[PDB]
Amino acid sequence: FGDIQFGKYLRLSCDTDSETLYELLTQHWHLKTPNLVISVTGGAK
């Protein structure tokens, strides 16, 4: 848990279901989405 300052980060197991993640990130945090964009890059150093 906890903030980062130089945002809210989190260490998480891969085996959790996505619904508790979404309920966390919408209820305890900011609101819903009319849209959702995905960019894939990260092998590009």
Image (cartoon, rainbow, N blue to C red):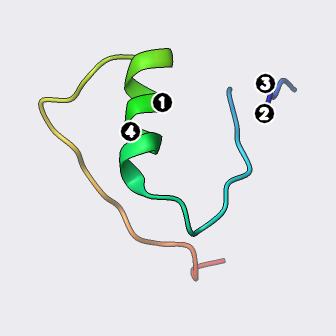
Residue under label 1, please give it.
24
Q: What's the distance in space between the residues labelled 2 and 3, CA to CA?
A: 7 Å
In-image side of 8 versus 27 (left or right)? right
Residue on which the image places disc 3: 3
Above or below: residue 27 compared with residue 37: above
30 vs 12, nearest the viewer: 12
Q: Position of residue 3 (x, y in %)?
A: 78, 24
Residue 6 is situated, as x and y percent measured from the top left of the image, at 87, 26
Q: Are marks 1 and 4 in contact (CB under 8 Å)?
A: yes
Mark 4: which amino acid? Tyr
Query: Dot 2 lies on which element?
Result: loop
How dense is the environment of label 4, judged by Cα within 10 Å: few (below 14), some, or many (20 and up)?
few
Q: Residue at x 50, y 17 (%)?
A: 28
Is residue 29 something one can see in this rendering?
Answer: no
Disc on res. 22:
4
> Which badge, 4 or 2, comes first in the chain's sequence?
2
Provide the residue designation for mark 2: 1
